[PDB]
Image (cartoon, rainbow over all chains, first blue to last red; front, side):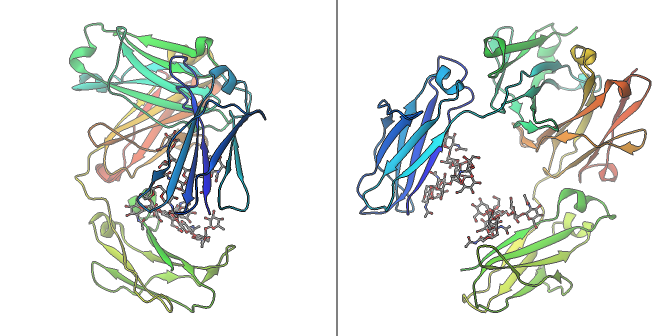
Length: 208
Length: 208
Ligand SMILES: *[C@@H]1O[C@H](CO[C@@H]2O[C@@H](C)[C@@H](O)[C@@H](O)[C@@H]2O)[C@@H](O[C@@H]2O[C@H](CO)[C@@H](O[C@@H]3O[C@H](CO[C@H]4O[C@H](CO)[C@@H](O)[C@H](O)[C@@H]4O[C@@H]4O[C@H](CO)[C@@H](O)[C@H](O)[C@H]4NC(C)=O)[C@@H](O)[C@H](O[C@H]4O[C@H](CO)[C@@H](O)[C@H](O)[C@@H]4O[C@@H]4O[C@H](CO)[C@@H](O)[C@H](O)[C@H]4NC(C)=O)[C@@H]3O)[C@H](O)[C@H]2NC(C)=O)[C@H](O)[C@H]1NC(C)=O
Ligand SMILES: *[C@@H]1O[C@H](CO[C@@H]2O[C@@H](C)[C@@H](O)[C@@H](O)[C@@H]2O)[C@@H](O[C@@H]2O[C@H](CO)[C@@H](O[C@@H]3O[C@H](CO[C@H]4O[C@H](CO)[C@@H](O)[C@H](O)[C@@H]4O[C@@H]4O[C@H](CO)[C@@H](O)[C@H](O)[C@H]4NC(C)=O)[C@@H](O)[C@H](O[C@H]4O[C@H](CO)[C@@H](O)[C@H](O)[C@@H]4O[C@@H]4O[C@H](CO)[C@@H](O)[C@H](O)[C@H]4NC(C)=O)[C@@H]3O)[C@H](O)[C@H]2NC(C)=O)[C@H](O)[C@H]1NC(C)=O
């Protein structure tokens, strides 16, 4: 029979208010004369009606896959609202309800540390500036790099890494050209998380 | 019908003689009264007869799961030898050949750097020393931390991270009580990977 998969908004949508944090409910495995199924949504047990439900998409494996996206506020999601996608079929003994919400647990503020290169690497053609971030719970978080004010193109971030106390940690690397490093340019890692002042913090450094 | 999953030896075991590196062939979904099945092993198209096989392990979900552990040398694996576990069944008609071998690609030497704490952190009651390993390939790699010879209990390590050029990178944090950091001690990272001198390299640092 068919199967439901409810998904959470992005750790970056949930924090900033320019983007829209959304909650996506998905159905799969709806056979070929199973008529339309119907999203009933509920937030903490009351029916909202603003979910932009989409059409009935065909799949390579000849199934029907259905989606309903539902916009939510950041206030709401981070207050621990319990969002629910109920689905009735036309050809299924039951209706299927799934529910989702923010992670439970006393949120913990990280602290950011920029780290410089190593005195070994400074002679190299490029160098690796390091943003260590640690102590953060919940695991959902976001990092960016900017330079003089202008944002940075290329960098790489590890997935969060569970720590021995139950907090999470991660590292982020930034390759910068040996050329561009020296002339006292100034570089800054910036981090977004539930438990920050303005949900936002930066460290920064120079060639000192 | 039944399915066959072949699995390689882990990087640590592939890198030193002390340990024994193994190639594991696992069949799952051998049904209720379908009798035994055989492993026919081959190495680059020649049959070896040394796999320490175990007998049929029945599962919760009511199938028969079978395993054969074949042992290899390290020179064998790093020469890129192709190992195959073929399965005769007494049920579904076919043989099921499955093949495994080392990752293809010109190996790259991991360049490793210890990084000290950040000035910021020092007033905390613990500190975080950082081993950064970059530019390595294949992704199979092992990191350990020791101090005055003795190894370390707490050390976390990110899973490798694909880089913009195709090499991999990773980080490792070591938390040490500040009571251990600042009375004159020496600390050391240790890295293992095929494209190295003696498949092993280490950096080290101290309160200078
Ligand atoms: C027919 O095809 C469809 C379409 O898929 C396509 O089919 C064929 C043609 C191939 O080409 C496929 O390669 C192709 O993808 C099949 O639909 C699939 O159905 C399976 C189930 O049979 C679903 O499995 C689930 O997967 C989700 C993860 O799905 C996300 O991530 C995938 C990649 O990571 C991505 O492909 C998906 O589209 C989806 O992607 C994310 O989507 C969100 C929302 O849009 C988006 O914001 C993200 O950015 C995006 N991410 C990425 C990386 O793209 C997974 O969550 C499920 O795991 C849980 O459930 C398992 C039980 O099935 C269980 O074993 C797990 O341990 C895990 O347990 C859960 O844990 C959660 C969280 O930790 C927790 O709440 C619970 O404890 C627990 N919950 C549950 C319910 O168990 C699950 O594995 C596929 O998502 C789905 N694919 C697509 C594309 O929709 C269909 O099955 C096929 N039918 C047949 C008969 O074969
Ligand atoms: C009945 O149950 C059994 C037992 O499982 C258990 O059953 C129930 C009771 C629950 O408790 C389960 O939670 C529990 O697991 C079922 O047996 C399972 O069968 C499925 C297949 O149906 C297997 O799926 C495959 O999984 C492997 C990974 O398996 C490793 O990792 C698991 C955890 O991550 C671990 O549980 C396994 O034991 C095994 O563990 C590893 O083992 C090695 C060797 O011993 C060891 O060195 C490792 O340290 C160890 N690791 C860990 C973390 O423990 C996965 O590789 C497969 O994925 C490939 O294939 C998929 C398609 O099947 C495909 O979607 C993927 O993309 C992927 O692609 C392959 O890989 C590469 C890279 O992508 C690609 O280049 C290849 O070309 C491609 N090849 C193929 C062929 O696809 C796959 O997902 C389970 O492992 C297996 N579980 C166990 C424990 O054996 C049984 O199926 C059940 N039967 C029924 C009817 O329900």
